[PDB]
Amino acid sequence: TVPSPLADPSIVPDPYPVYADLAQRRPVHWVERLNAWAVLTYADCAAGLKDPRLTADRGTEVLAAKFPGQPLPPDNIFHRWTKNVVMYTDPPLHDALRRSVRAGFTRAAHQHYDQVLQKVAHDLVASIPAGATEIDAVPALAAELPVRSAVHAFGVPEEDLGFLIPRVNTIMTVTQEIILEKLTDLHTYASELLQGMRGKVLPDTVIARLAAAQDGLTETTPEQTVHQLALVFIALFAPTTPGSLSSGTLAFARNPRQVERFLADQACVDNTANEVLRYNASNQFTWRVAAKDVEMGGVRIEAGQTLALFLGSANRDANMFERPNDFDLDRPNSARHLSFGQGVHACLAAQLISLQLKWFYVALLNRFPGIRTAGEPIWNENLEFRSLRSLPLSLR
Ligand code: HEB
């Protein structure tokens, strides 16, 4: 019953040496407070994400872990939701649900999002007053860009932001019932939005393409589109994107050489998203459940037991990324990071987010190449969704 040096918040601002300590001896071990087997190496994490033996059907288990002794009946909104979205379903249902939303994520769509995001990022960074000298990059940039991308790339109506953001914030973090009510709000909003009963959806956006494709859907139901749209809203306004932006900004702030590498060579620019994502996973760990007994890292994981796959540790496994603690844009294989997961449930917005990141650093660094930290960066108290709460920055 030895507690794990994970679980405890003290490691959040810099969890990587701890990950290393543990990975040396105990790459797979029990975490008392997560009710789960933590797995830490790249090999076993990738294996975990690809394995048809671990199920994504994990709502009951994760909810147990997060709200002990507070079970929910199968017809409760949380369970219907989990049963009807890509995140918590296995093939073949998962594949049908995934195919039902591909209209927003085609090659052509991303061709458009590229231009849109170039624009948005440039306007954001250009909006910084010419004599600024100091900034907290978290509220000013990292928290702001995903919102603007949500409006102009995804198609969330601007006027509806004030409805959606507090509700996702509540969901992501008081009471389980309040969270359930907010999730219900997200479903009802998705439903009414598609019927034109809410804000105006800008054209050529994700939600516009999704809406136009509803009449052509044959394997899935309107209800399932509502569920998945609720999921989309949650991921859209989660701290994951701002966390990536801010952690990357901090990485550049502490690595001038990579700033000049960035400004000189287009290769570095094109690898920037992947290297930032590798250096700090916004989602430090994701969850699985063993459908059957699995043998991993020298451990017999029993059927029904929960697994915590530490993508953040895998991104800095020296077995896969030589000198993993270095922020390096010339790195050959940054694209092998697990920050977007891997295989079946690989992040639906991976390319959109990569575009957002790239253009953000292009715009930031073509105006402020002389960025430094001006005081200690402050991290949130959570490891699972790890992100900077404050990043004080001197621009000039
Ligand atoms: C659209 C909206 C959206 C956005 C914005 C996002 C953004 C993001 N994302 Fe995401 N995702 C998503 C949507 C999303 N997403 C979905 C829907 C999913 C599921 C898929 C499947 O399942 O198939 C994911 C998934 C996912 C995963 C996997 C998990 C598992 O497997 O379990 C990960 C790791 C991630 C991450 C992420 C990050 C880090 C970010 C920032 C940077 N993602």
Image (tube, grey):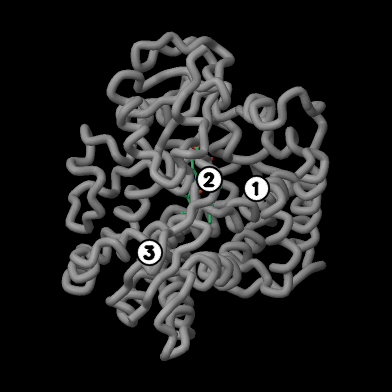
Quarter of the image where one finds residue 74 = top right
Tell me, for residue 385, which label it has, or none.
2
Query: The residue under label 2 is which amino acid type?
Result: Phe
Tell me, for residue 125, which label it has, or none.
none
Q: Find numbered disc 2 in the image and state the secondary structure of the residue it sits on.
A: loop
Q: Residues within 10 Å of mark 3 (few under 14, many from 20)?
A: many
Residue located beneath label 3 in the image:
249
Q: Is residue 64 left or right of residue 378?
A: right
Residue located beneath label 1 in the image:
172
Query: The residue under label 3 is which amino acid type?
Result: Thr
**Label 2 to label 3, Cα distance in Å?**
17 Å
The answer to whether residue 320 is seen in the rendering is yes
Q: Quadrant of the C terminus?
A: bottom left
Q: Are marks 2 and 3 in contact (CB under 8 Å)?
A: no
**Chain-order first, disc 3 or disc 1:** 1
**Label 3 to label 1, Cα distance in Å?**
23 Å
Asked if disc 1 is less than 8 Å from ligand 1, the answer is: no
At which x and y percent is residue 381? 55, 46
Residue at (40% x, 71% y) in the render: 393
**Chain-order first, disc 2 or disc 3:** 3
Quarter of the image where one finds residue 57 = top right
